[PDB]
Image: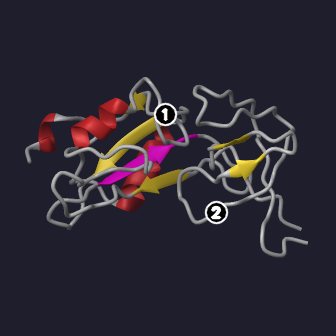
Amino acid sequence: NNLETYEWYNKSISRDKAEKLLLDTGKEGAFMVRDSRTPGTYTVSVFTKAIISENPCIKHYHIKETNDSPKRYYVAEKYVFDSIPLLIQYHQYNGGGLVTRLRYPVCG
Amino acid sequence: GSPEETLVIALYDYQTNDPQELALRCDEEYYLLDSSEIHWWRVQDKNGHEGYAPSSYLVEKSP
């Protein structure tokens, strides 16, 4: 899938760089994605200035891969999406199962 | 003292955006029923308000 079109998608970035890069934003909601070696199971790097023990903190919500049809990617046990662009958008607004409903994307 | 279930609290003043989510009153507190989840930790308000509460804004009180 050509995710290079989106912003949250970033393969040229690693976890360490993902955790730091997001830190630069220093904004609550700052969310992004990081390609994974898997054949189809990227990762949603969610950064939200929260937590007391460790702040800031990065939430690595690894899209639950459900090799089914449909049933594929999802992160909330609520609803399942057959694509990442949906899970990323469905959370942009409305409401879902996310510590900090996505509302602020990041880019390189 | 944190035997089987720990307790968490909201750092800021997170507000519920949906019935599913659990409203928090910066200073409130509850218990932990599902810490296995990476997103929400099904907590139970003393009043009886059970809902998905934000793990981030939350943190195990611990001893």
| In the image, residue B16 above or below residue A71 | above
Residue indicated by mark 1: A101
Magenta-highlighted stretch: main secondary structure? strand
Residue at 39%, 28% in the rendered image: A92
Q: Where, quadrant-wise, is the N terminus of chain B in this rendering? A: bottom right
The residue nearer to you, when weighing A62 against B50, is B50
Decide if residue A83 is on the left or right side of residue B23.
Answer: left
Q: Where, quadrant-wise, is the C terminus of chain B in this rendering? A: bottom right
Residue at 32%, 37% in the rendered image: A88
| Residue farthest along the bottom direction in this orientation | B3
The residue nearer to you, when weighing A6 against B27, is B27
| In the image, residue A6 above or below residue A65 | above
Residue B49 percent across, percent down from the top left: 76, 39
Query: Per the image, is B44 magenta?
Result: no
Quarter residue A104 falls in: top left
Residue A16 percent across, percent down from the top left: 41, 60
- Co-location on one chain, circles 2 and 1: no
In the rendered image, is residue A107 in sight?
no
Give the amino acid at mark 2.
Answer: Ser
Name the element at disc 1: loop
| In the image, residue A66 above or below residue A56 | below
Residues at circles 2 and 1 in contact by the CB criterion of under 8 Å: no
Residue A4 percent across, percent down from the top left: 13, 41
Mark 2–mark 1 Cα distance, whole angstroms, equals 19 Å
Q: Determine which of the numbered discs, if any, sits on residue B62 in the image.
A: none
Decide if residue A65 is on the left or right side of residue B37.
Answer: left
Q: Which range is magenta? A: A43-48
Residue A52 percent across, percent down from the top left: 74, 50
Give the amino acid at mark 1.
Answer: Arg
Residue indicated by mark 2: B35
